[PDB]
Image: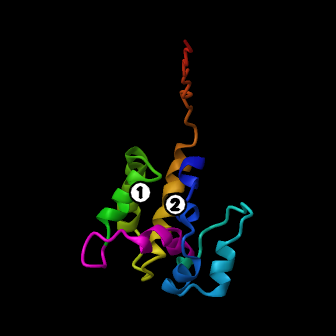
């Protein structure tokens, strides 16, 4: 859905060069990252996955002393972009797929194993009919 497809970092766009430096994104990644064509490929590079939550996270979102900013990052997402129900659909995959993920050490790539594990899950659900959010805004003048 376009809801969560509206990326916070894309909306912000406050500092491109400083997000570029912060992750030390190689030219190959940040370039492919800017691919505006909706190819819909598999997220293979950690620097891409990380850059998705780079703008609004490097702005301000640290729960603890600097590192391990888990709470505020999820709290920030629930207050801006995804409602609590969507974040709660993600957290479940995050915890289970990351826990069941192979011990291949790449801090940002693990987050990809869970991310793709989520669209895998939603794809297994596949057939889900919507109730249609029909809202009749009755504006009665005079």
Residue underneath mark 2: 8
**The one of 58 and 43 positioned closer to us in this rendering:** 58
Question: Mark 2 and 1 residues: CB-CB less than 8 Å, in contact?
Answer: yes
Residue 96 seen by the camera: no
Give left or right: position of 27 versus 128: right
Crowding around mark 2 (Cα neighbors within 10 Å: few <14, some 14 to 19, many 20+) is some
Residue 77 is tagged as 1
> Residue at coordinates 31% horizontally, 79% vertically from top-left?
67
Label 2, secondary structure: give it: helix
| Residue at horizontal 67 percent and vertical 65 percent from the top | 41
Badge 1, how many Cα within 10 Å: few under 14, some, many 20+?
A: some
Q: Position of residue 126 (x, y in %)?
A: 57, 43
Q: Which one is nearer the viewer's eye here, 75 or 94? A: 75
Residue 104 place in picture, x, y as percent: 44, 81
Q: Which residues are magenta?
A: 48-68
Q: x and y percent of residue 9 in the render?
A: 53, 65
The CA span between labels 2 and 1 is 9 Å
Picture layout, residue 67 above or below residue 116: below
Vertical order, 118 against 13 (above or below): above
Residue under the point 42% across and 46% down: 83
Q: Quick one: 133 or 105, which is closer to the camera? A: 133
Image: 97 above or below 50: above
Q: Quadrant of the C terminus?
A: top right
- Would you say residue 62 sits in the magenta stretch? yes
Q: Identify the coloring.
A: rainbow
Q: Position of residue 34 (x, y in %)?
A: 67, 72
SS for callout 1? helix
Q: Earlier in the sequence, mark 2 or mark 1?
A: 2
């Amino acid at each position: 859905s376009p809801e969560i497809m509206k990326n916070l970092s894309n909306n912000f766009g406050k500092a491109m060069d400083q997000c570029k430096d912060e992750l030390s994104l190689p030219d190959s990644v940040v370039a492919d990252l800017y691919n505006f064509w909706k190819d819909d490929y598999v997220m293979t590079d950690r620097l891409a996955g990380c850059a998705i939550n780079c703008l609004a996270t490097k702005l301000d979102v640290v729960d603890p002393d600097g590192n391990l900013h888990h709470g505020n990052a999820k709290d920030f997402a629930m207050k801006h972009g995804a409602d609590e129900t969507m974040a709660q659909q993600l957290v479940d995959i995050i915890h289970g797929c990351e826990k069941s993920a192979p011990p291949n050490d790449d801090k940002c790539m693990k987050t990809i194993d869970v991310a793709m594990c989520f669209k895998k899950e939603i794809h297994k659900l596949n057939w889900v009919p919507n109730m249609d959010l029909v809202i009749g805004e009755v504006l009665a003048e005079v």
